[PDB]
Amino acid sequence: DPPLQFHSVHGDNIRISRDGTLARRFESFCRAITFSARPVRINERICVKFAEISNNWNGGIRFGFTSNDPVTLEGTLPKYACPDLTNRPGFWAKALHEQYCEKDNILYYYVNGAGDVIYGINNEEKGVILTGIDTRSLLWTVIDIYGNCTGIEFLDS
Ligand SMILES: [Mg+2]
Image (cartoon, rainbow, N blue to C red; front, side, top):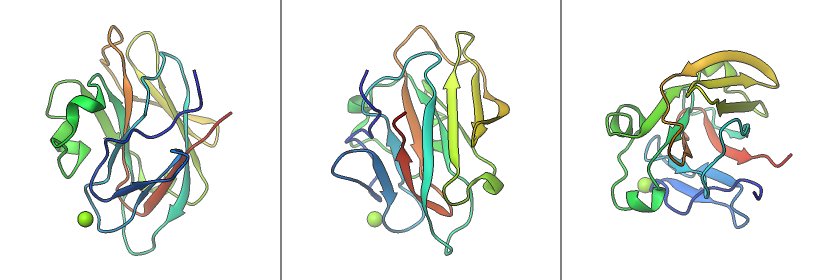
């Protein structure tokens, strides 16, 4: 439907912009978990821009999907998507290589009918990063704003 926004259920170290399109890890190095405000479609491309980078932290963001309505998760969020959420049923996420986490890159990803998650950077496919996603339930993005990237923007095309 409408352009993707961040869910109001998020980590303690996250601030979301007024229009809901920009999530920042405002302090520290963890508790940086975020979700999409609405479920996403199979084959819908999620496009995220690395809007802000800190030179004081290293590492890549973690991204993927959850079959859990983020409202059901409030007061329940751990420090990390990996391993902490991924250990629970209905979360699929992996780290993005830190070489891709540079200012103004666009990460795109989607889950296909087969339940595989394909990703790329600046419109160049990198491949399948995740497999076995439950395509029979509603899915929300999970993006853990970990590492040198401290601000990410959902892009509207
Ligand atoms: Mg804090």
